[PDB]
Image: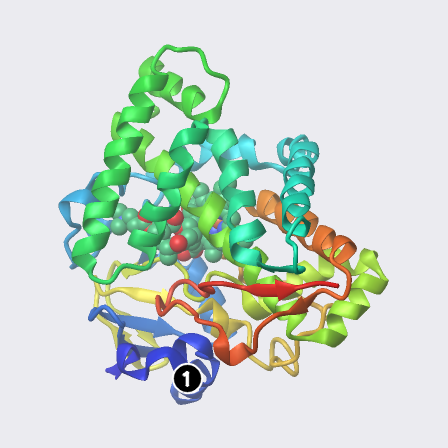
Amino acid sequence: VLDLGALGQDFAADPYPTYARLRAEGPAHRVRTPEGDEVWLVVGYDRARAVLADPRFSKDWRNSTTPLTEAEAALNHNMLESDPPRHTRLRKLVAREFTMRRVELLRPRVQEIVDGLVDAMLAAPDGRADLMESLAWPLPITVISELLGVPEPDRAAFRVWTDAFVFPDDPAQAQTAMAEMSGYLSRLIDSKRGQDGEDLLSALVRTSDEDGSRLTSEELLGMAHILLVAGHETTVNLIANGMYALLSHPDQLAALRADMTLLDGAVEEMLRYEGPVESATYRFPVEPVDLDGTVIPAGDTVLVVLADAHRTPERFPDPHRFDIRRDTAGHLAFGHGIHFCIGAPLARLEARIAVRALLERCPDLALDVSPGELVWYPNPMIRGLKALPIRWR
Ligand code: HEM
Ligand SMILES: CC[C@H]1OC(=O)[C@H](C)[C@@H](OC(=O)CCN(C)C)[C@@H](C)C[C@@H](C)C(=O)/C=C/[C@H]1C
């Protein structure tokens, strides 16, 4: 049992040499997380990709030997914490909302949001700002909030609850937060009921009312939760981590600023090199699974380490090089298999717009701090910064 809490901020900041040295010793390893839970890491690209798609590794908490808390059990009837056939049905509900076509329709508004956020940011008197406060955070919360129908006065609460259960001081504190947000969401579902809003939460509340067999009240709260947590948190971190990647590689920043057709590939390499999902969501083996002689017990918690997958040199040569022109095909930053990210085109749309606007409107854009002054969150599932100080000319 490697104690990841004991490794401290050095591991949070640069966990890669740790995964890589585990990977050399075998595909799977028992570790304790900073919070105190024993889990399994699965490392190495080929094994990570296999495990992600393998039906022996379930997402349904009934297959876990760790009981849900009260507040969590209110929230688990969502597609990411389901297996077929419930998974199949939940995913089909919101299928269509996230295609490249429906997301294309959002390009104008996404642009307008960024255009505005970037205005405000430039109005800074000394040409200095924290990219997280100025753009990384507000852009995704705003986009997802409009989609779902979270009214403007309530959106502030989401950062706090989200930070609370994504990065708490104690598990006891995430509980309260989740209860509180879940409390909020029920009340927001109830407020939509038969009120004829055109947002997705109203469309879903409709579905549940019409045919509570296609969608239960509980699945309604779960779906609302899930769409909110990805639509801001991971996307915020893609934006901030990928900009950090660009800023700390002055050479690749110049290369993209010189040629914007390089943009889609740059965003892919930011997903590869500094993706916000360090480790995929909990997997639970239905039966014991032997991984090249290392047997994981049924019901244990298994974290597939996407970050280590992406530094696997036989898959991504010279893995420690951030190279915007690199072949990134087949990366796992949006997962793999039947739980593959539904929001991937939206995440991509937002990041691409945000990066282009920063490069085009912030002259001599640069990191305003040294890498050693950055603070990364210890949660082994999320790769993310506390602040990103930037400056421009
Ligand atoms: C950069 C941004 C994003 C990244 C890196 C990301 C990554 C991921 C990953 C790795 C998974 C699979 C988790 C696993 O297999 O354990 C996932 C699934 C999921 N994502 Fe995203 N995602 C992002 C943005 C979004 C957005 C904007 C939305 C909302 C539209 C969203 C909604 C979902 C949903 C509902 C699932 C569950 C899918 C299923 O179970 O079939 N994601 N995503
Ligand atoms: C939908 C994609 C998104 O995943 C999530 O929202 C996680 C499911 C979500 O986990 C839960 O909601 C737990 C609820 N059960 C305990 C009841 C999220 C908080 C996990 C976290 C690693 C993340 O930010 C994860 C973000 C992405 C991986």
> Dot 1 corresponds to which residue?
18
Q: Give the position of the N terminus as an image quadrant.
A: bottom left
Q: Residue furthest front?
A: 125
Residue 272 image offset from top left, x and y in percent: 59, 67
The quarter of the picture where residue 77 lies is top left
Residue 20 image offset from top left, x and y in percent: 46, 84
Residue 167 image offset from top left, x and y in percent: 32, 59
Residue 212: in sight, yes or no? no
275, above or below 190, in the image? below
The quarter of the picture where residue 228 lies is top left
The residue lying toward the viewer, choosing from 284 and 142, is 142
Residue at the image point whose x is 49% and y is 63% from the top: 387
The residue lying toward the viewer, choosing from 114 and 14, is 114
Q: Residues within 10 Å of mark 1 (few under 14, many from 20)?
A: some
In this rendering, position of residue 158 left or right of residue 105: left
Residue 203: in sight, yes or no? yes
Q: Residue furthest right?
A: 258
Residue 352 image offset from top left, x and y in percent: 68, 51
Q: Does the Cβ of the disc 1 residue fall within 8 Å of ligand 2? A: no
369, above or below 79, in the image? below
Which amino acid is tagged 1? Answer: Thr
Residue at the image point whose x is 75% and y is 63% from the top: 393
Residue at the image point whose x is 71% and y is 73% from the top: 323
In this rendering, position of residue 161 left or right of residue 376: left
The residue lying toward the viewer, choosing from 333 and 351, is 351
In this rendering, position of residue 101 left or right of residue 46: right
Q: Is mark 1 on a helix, strand or loop?
A: helix
Residue at the image point whose x is 76% and y is 66% from the top: 364
